[PDB]
Image 1 (spheres, one colour):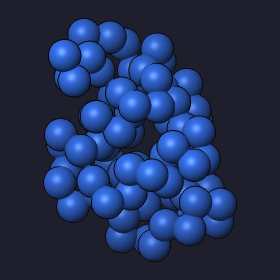
Image 2: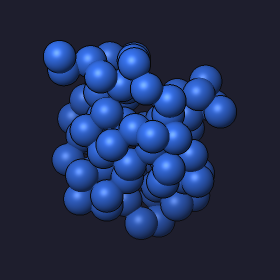
Image 3: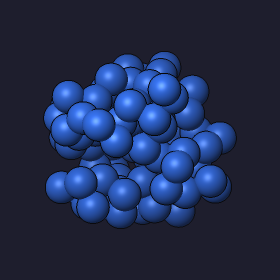
Length: 76
């Protein structure tokens, strides 16, 4: 239903599925959902993202950026 990210490979995730992944794995990051929409971060983009980019272009603070980076590491 609203958990389609579970039934698809990260590389094929849509922006909404990326947000789904983040929300479900760390509630404290749910607030940044609109950032991924604004910067159009789908699955393919997520796998190319790094902390410096998130801070420089997405306006994320170091803490959240590191936490997101950690979630990305789990899915490579």
